[PDB]
Length: 11
Image 1 (cartoon, rainbow, N blue to C red):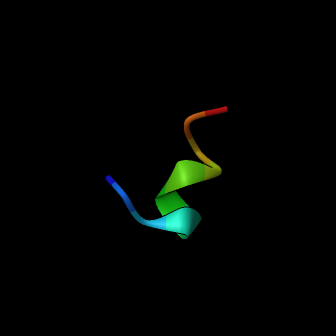
Image 2 (tube, rainbow, N blue to C red):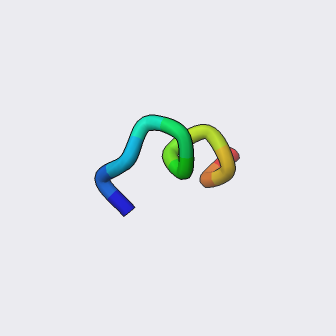
């Protein structure tokens, strides 16, 4: 998602 929290999981 566009969320920064979930954005970290993208890694």
